[PDB]
Amino acid sequence: VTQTMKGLDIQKVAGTWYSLAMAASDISLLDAQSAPLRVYVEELKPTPEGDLEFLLQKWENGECAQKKIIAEKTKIPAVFKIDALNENKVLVLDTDYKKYLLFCMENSAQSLACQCLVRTPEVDDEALEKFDKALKALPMHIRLSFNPTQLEEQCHI
Amino acid sequence: VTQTMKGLDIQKVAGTWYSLAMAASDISLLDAQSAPLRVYVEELKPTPEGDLEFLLQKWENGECAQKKIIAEKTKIPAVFKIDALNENKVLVLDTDYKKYLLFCMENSAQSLACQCLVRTPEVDDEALEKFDKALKALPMHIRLSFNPTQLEEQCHI
Image (cartoon, each protein chain N blue to C red):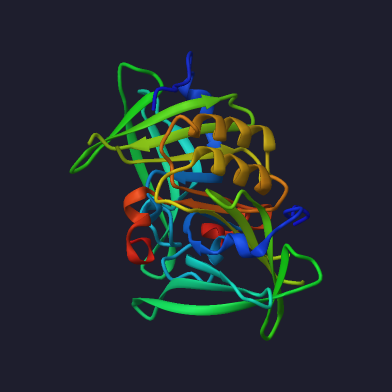
């Protein structure tokens, strides 16, 4: 992934989002309702100090659970770090702040998952074209997209 | 689906194939290794009388099973019928016989699953472009593609 957002203003990504579409390098990362990177964005919350908190939904042990994760800032405005047992990165690819945002999460070995976020529960063909433009430069093997009904449900049921 | 293969010669599709890629209208039809339309082609066998037999693999009750289904001919050369509890159709979209073949299976209510077949275990970008050309005219919400290692395994493990 060598497409980041030039001139990103992190504070302007704040608020409500919908995961309209998702893609990953490996089928198993997104294949089931409880696959490990089948995570749905609810809200992005930039911090005063410049870190990026994600509020997420995920299907975990037979139900739709909530969870807050903090991605810490780097010297590069469009790149954040979630460092657990591995060093993983969050990259903001492109946004216009008021309609869409593209991001990826990636490991450091090679393995990758990206999403098209939108501000409202509708299919934005334009935002989806920019997503597919970004993805043709990456080795994705599975792609999912959601309908407006699903987008208004918990865990996109 | 309003893309069929003009001038199809059914007998020439005979022999070995690989399911390089699959797409469907509904996420649940392809989402798990045991999803109901996650079926892998092994061989197409046209009959003397002009019907089309598929030899398939599918993951069923924790293992990789074999199964033979017969799709019966119609007055339209590129359209065959699998009629169980519902009337379902097999449509041949496009082929050159010696490298690729695109087909869909569809119900009569609206619900749809299509595949890109290739003759050899390799990623054929050209064949994949024709597949994605066909799919942009259809309401697909999930897409899978397989690597050469996976294509040489039973049930694409």
